[PDB]
Amino acid sequence: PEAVARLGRVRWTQQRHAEAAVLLQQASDAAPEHPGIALWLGHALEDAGQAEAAAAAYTRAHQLLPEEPYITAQLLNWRRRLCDWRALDVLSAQVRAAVAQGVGAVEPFAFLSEDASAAEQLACARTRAQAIAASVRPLAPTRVRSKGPLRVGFVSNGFGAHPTGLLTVALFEALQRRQPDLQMHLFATSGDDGSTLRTRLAQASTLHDVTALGHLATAKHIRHHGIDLLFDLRGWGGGGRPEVFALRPAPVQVNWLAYPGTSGAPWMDYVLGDAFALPPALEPFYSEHVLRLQGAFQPSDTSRVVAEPPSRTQCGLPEQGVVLCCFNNSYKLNPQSMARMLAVLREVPDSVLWLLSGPGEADARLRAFAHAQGVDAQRLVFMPKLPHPQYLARYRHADLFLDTHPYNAHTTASDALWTGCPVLTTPGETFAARVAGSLNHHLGLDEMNVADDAAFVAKAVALASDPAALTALHARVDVLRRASGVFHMDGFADDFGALLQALARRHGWLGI
Ligand SMILES: O=C1NC(=O)C(=O)C(=O)N1
Image (cartoon, rainbow, N blue to C red; front, side):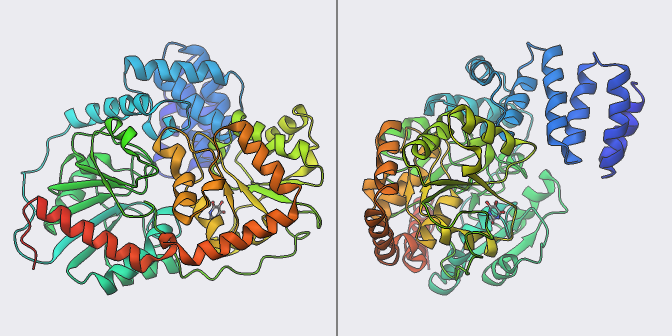
């Protein structure tokens, strides 16, 4: 059992994931009390795409080492992803308690899913950042160059058909064309996926494939290019590499557009946000010194021709009736967010709720939940996984997009609005809970940022039972869509590049 588990750990290392699971299973069966085993069976199954089973292992892992914070955090994040709300209140309290005593175990990105103040979030991101910052030894300090073309770098694991590259690409294209004085460098931590996004990016910047490399080497590689300002678009989220940034390969390091919160990190100099999503009230809760673009913090791909979707029926929708949708990551679909969406459904009879098909049995769960809330399960409709262009097309059948709290739709909110679908949100009290709000505000749709849950249901019921007002809202989105600066990458470029040159001067750049 102790041996098995390690062979199967070997299999794990050499992507023979299928057998890793069958070995680790064989171990777990024979020694069902061994927490370390339960724990490896769990990462095993997960990476063999057996979600439900994977989470079952973390449950037992938790039953065996109840006082263990890291396991508890891992279990909660797994249950959110599967929309399994058994004991969510307790689990959520333990994770927050850990952060408070931290130790250390809560991953900051998972933590974004919790009902937690901007303060707890800072505590959490600082605690993590510290354990990393200590175990590492920074590279020889350097300074922003005095003379010349400013070298600006961005590191990300989604350059290509992913959120990051998918938001930044028209931006990178505008900057090549409008900000010649800036030299744009993309350090891509994932390989060429053959997406036209990946080509475009490579065509608009100098794209370095550092996918082969390790933390130390990556830093050293960035430093080889003598990058003056280095943007972390990663951020505490999956596909590393914070330890890269801890080596401070660049003398100025900016947290932007990727991780919707503070880094808590001593190696991170600036965060870039906006007046709305990061307002003065919230600055004390950022370790970075705050910068702000003139408009919304988020760019997007303003060349996308939204395609034509298949008929409502071929998309599983009925023909008449309002389609309110919430395309978002499953972990964001919390009890509070589902309740308020289902409340709309109850009071507006005709009507339907369109969701992304989640992992494991998430969809069965949300069905059963809808029924518990006294709503026909048939009225939830689930979209499968689809290439961006076909996915993006689906918003054409959407009537109103209903945001989640406390972790807003981010790229999906930008996607809706671009296709012309209004987005309803309740801007909360942390950056991540204010991303929709900031798009709406900057687009001019303040009436779509409402105060609380009751207001959310009220506004949505208003729109859903008055198609006249609803059709007119779309019309309004459309005007605002082409006239606000939110979707003017050209202006966004000019803004960014100027704010970039400014930062550079403060750290002693003499331009030219
Ligand atoms: O481009 C996307 N394709 C998807 O299938 C999806 O779920 C999403 O959020 N974004």
